[PDB]
Image 1 (cartoon, chains in turn blue, orange, purple):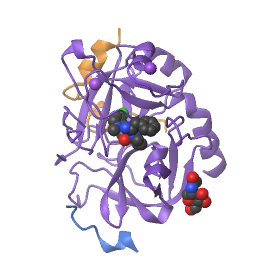
Image 2: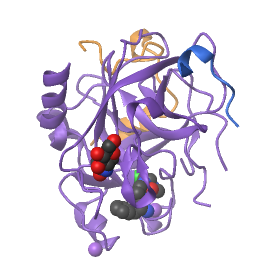
Image 3: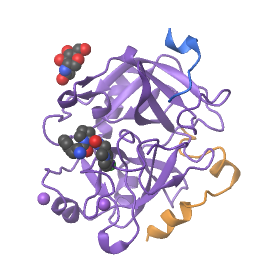
Image 4: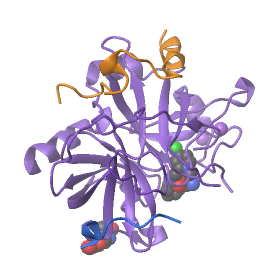
Length: 11
Length: 28
Length: 251
Ligand SMILES: C[n+]1ccc(Cl)cc1CNC(=O)[C@@H]1CCCN1C(=O)[C@H](N)Cc1ccccc1
Ligand SMILES: *[C@@H]1O[C@H](CO)[C@@H](O)[C@H](O)[C@H]1NC(C)=O
Ligand code: NA
Ligand code: NA
């Protein structure tokens, strides 16, 4: 349902 | 912050949002 | 938010979305009170009856948002959490007394047209504004109905309610650390916070200095927008000594 967020914020 | 609670797109440019007057009218 | 409307762009630039990393979903609302500090409800982070006990690494904060689900490239900013602080006397066992928490960000967020902190009330602000009939404003991306979900941030203006009326509306024990807001059945108008709006701000615009103050935090209600029920909000000023203690010690 949510658009993916940039990978840098999930590191 | 000295600038807290003043919105860039409203208070900062002296524009009012569509319903803030409803709040003001309740402050009797 | 039930029976509210779409926010205007930049209408609530202190609005924060607490975002779960996995699965990716809305966890709660919150508010920006400085470049490094975010205010929310304790039950957004800690609520054992629902097996909720988040750690810093479980969550992200998304600031400057309007769309609920979109990644708002070049507008929103996403911050990691350095540390969570929950009120030491938060009562999750009974009635959500002292339903308040702070989150310190790993790095300061840059303010913009869409990102800007709200003021916290002092004693005089609170005395002047926290009166029955005076309206505040609640915002969030929570459910549109008790039993769906909004495209963009929702807003509703609601009147503060007399304490005895709040007390008589529920069997739950109310405390001085709470206030309630909403329309009565006889009043026709409606509106309430709901699931997902938890932790977001109840704000009032001071007619004395034209600044927005966060008087409450979305805390609890029996259902959403039910006739004869009201929403309950953490009384921010009553708990401000704790807020200041935490920021002074850890900031
Ligand atoms: C659902 N709703 C309605 C109005 C407002 Cl202003 C906020 C909320 C969201 N809050 C909630 O859903 C909170 C989280 C835990 C249970 N809860 C509730 O609101 C419970 N429905 C009522 C309750 C209050 C105090 C203690 C235990 C249960
Ligand atoms: C919540 O999590 C912490 C550990 O991360 C734990 O020590 C605590 O007992 C848990 N329950 C609380 C704080 O009620
Ligand atoms: Na009662
Ligand atoms: Na109601």
